[PDB]
Image (cartoon, coloured by chain):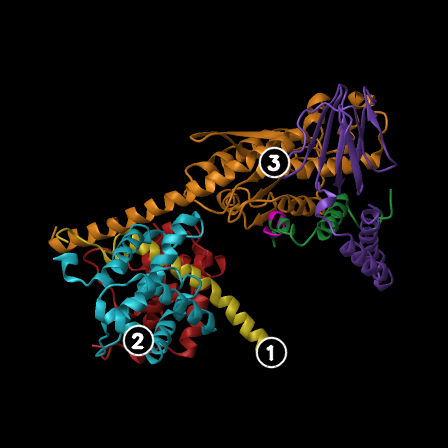
Chain colours: A orange, B yellow, C green, D red, E cyan, F purple
Amino acid sequence: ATLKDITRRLKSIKNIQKITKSMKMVAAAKYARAERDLKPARVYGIGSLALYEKADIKVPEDKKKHLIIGVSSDRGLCGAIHSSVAKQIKSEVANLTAAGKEVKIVGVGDKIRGILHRTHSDQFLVTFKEVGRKPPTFGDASVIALELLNSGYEFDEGSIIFNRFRSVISYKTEEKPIFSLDTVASAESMSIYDDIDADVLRNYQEYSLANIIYYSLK
Amino acid sequence: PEGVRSGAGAVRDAGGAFGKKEQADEERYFRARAREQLAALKKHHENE
Amino acid sequence: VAYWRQAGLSYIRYSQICAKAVRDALKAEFKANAEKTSGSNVKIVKVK
Amino acid sequence: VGSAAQTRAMKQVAGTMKLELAQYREVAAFALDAATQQLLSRGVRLTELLKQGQYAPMAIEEQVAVIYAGVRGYLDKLEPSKITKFENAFLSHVISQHQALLGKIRADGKISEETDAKLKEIVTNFLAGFEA
Amino acid sequence: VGSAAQTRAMKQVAGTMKLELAQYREVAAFAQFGSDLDAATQQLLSRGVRLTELLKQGQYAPMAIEEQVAVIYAGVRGYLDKLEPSKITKFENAFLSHVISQHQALLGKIRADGKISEETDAKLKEIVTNFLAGFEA
Amino acid sequence: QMSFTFASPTQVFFNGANVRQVDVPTQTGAFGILASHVPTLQVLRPGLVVVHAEDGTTSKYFVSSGSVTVNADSSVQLLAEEAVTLDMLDPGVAKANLEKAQSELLGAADEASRAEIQIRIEANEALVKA
């Protein structure tokens, strides 16, 4: 309650305000470029998934477990971006374990690994790093997909969770299914296509995985 | 000129929450690197 | 099945190789697309 | 005073507690496992040892023993919430069943190899038996 | 009192120097993270940091007026944009000696008349380009 | 009677455009697409793709790898990792790369690395034709 304490406390906040004010413009400048490149990638991402849309494919009741993928960055100060994804990641596993499967979780982004480490340390299969400092590219999705197949773990089902840009002031959390299993792909509705083979379908699922990963990051 | 003008390092002079929060982060970050540097010193000296 | 298959090579690896080979043949003026590709920015940290 | 007037036995176990608390304070306040987690795991134990009641001072050798238990790491496994009960029960047991050991520390004024050998066995046995 | 106590020659250069140094102060906070900015802001930062280095001076060594005018003239025209900031002082030191040793009659006109005429401007334009080309770091 | 979309991870060439036919150098031989072709799903190989416009002009592009999909209707999605035009290419550097890749075959020791080298020489020999 002396004069010196008041002076020091005023002089600290005077600097904090200017630091935040200068940090706002950089995020606006980055958001402009981030918005610019979304449109060319949206059509590619939608075009990748047309086949699964036209011919409905439903997974059966098997026990090969899932492969849940969550996407985030390594930086904070972004409101509740990471918490929303980490909320649904732990919600799905309860339903999955109700049936009983050897589910594993793979997360790209350090914050996702940090938040859920305490209660789901064993289910972690592999994690990535160095995300968000520079804009993502297709090569990163290629590297992730390449490193994902070499794992000895095999799955019949899987899903990927991400935040979808809706407006400059709002966003929506959603997930998309993966039917990359060859056996479930070979169903009645696929009989219309009449130049297929096992090798061709294996390569086709291989490519669809990288396409979905790139679309989610962008 | 009449008002209160701030300077450099005023955040760590008041000794509030932000000063100690600032100090602990530097302490951790530079506590991490010394292990790698010592391990590389031992490997270098053992090699030659 | 081709020679690349049954040789430890995946379709993604083959696509990477062919894309790199095509990008090499470009004129030096247009070689700024290597900046756009820049596929190496993600590190890998295993469980152990 | 620079600890010019202090018993020899107390210096051995207090000079090492100074460093533990000095290094605990500089990091463990943020309003990895190799260094940081161990550091505050030891520091939270060391803080709880210094609390004390009212109208009940202690003799020097009993303080030496109770600090000797903490500093060496014999209590790095127990949850911090239950440390005080361990202190009380261990002090009562040591006072009753080992009256000859305290006299050695009081008379000599310093610890010895035989005393150090005895204390580890006493501490480990009582810790094993004291789980309630 | 202001500009009423300046010679005609100093006034022309100091008028532009004043505005160029006034613009730099309001964007100096952005200097820490300036990479993620447009070109317009980075140009103000670049010119301001060049102009700051010229105002440094030694001790017990005052200058003359025409030498100050000659030094500032190169600064305000953009002839020092490509140089790295670490080498501004050495360039000033060398340029003053070169102009003093040979080009004395030019300084005589600036000292005498007190204003920069057209032909003197034309001569200075060639002098600075020649020396800058020959500096070779 | 067609909706053709020749997209890339970077830019877009067509979006729902209507053309008479498209020729694709896919795996397992060449191909020809017109009117209501039978459904198919095939990956590509390094080669040249030509698209015949309704007016009659033919546009050409070079594709490295990707996927082809012709659905029940006359909707075709051709998504390629690479999409380039010859005007930004150098034939001489292509011949030099081929010349080095030739000796790289004998330089190789293990069959997997030589398989990678074979993919290299396959790509280099494919592109130098045009």
Which of labels 2 and 3 is toward the front? 2
Q: Position of residue D101 (x, y in %)?
A: 36, 72
Q: Position of residue A184 (x, y in %)?
A: 75, 28
Q: Which residue is mark 1?
A: B46
In the image, F7: left or right of F116? Answer: left
Q: CA distance from mark 3 to mark 1?
A: 49 Å
Secondary element at image label 3: helix
Q: Which residue is mark 2?
A: E105
Looking at the rendered structure, the kind of residue marked 2 is Ala
Give, as a single range, the part of the protein colored magenta: C36-43
Determine the image quadrant of residue A192: top right
Looking at the rendered structure, the kind of residue marked 1 is Glu
Secondary element at image label 1: helix
Q: Nearer the viewer, residue F66 or F52?
A: F52
CB under 8 Å between callouts 3 and 1? no
CB under 8 Å between callouts 2 and 3? no
**Mark 1 Cα shell of 10 Å, populated few (<14), some (14-19), many (≥20):** few
Q: Which labelled disc corresponds to residue D59? A: none
Which of labels 3 and 1 is toward the front? 3
Q: Nearer the viewer, residue B20 or E99?
A: E99
Looking at the rendered structure, the kind of residue marked 3 is Tyr
The quadrant of the picture occupied by the N terminus of chain D is bottom left
**Mark 2 Cα shell of 10 Å, populated few (<14), some (14-19), many (≥20):** few
Q: Nearer the viewer, residue A50 or A74?
A: A50
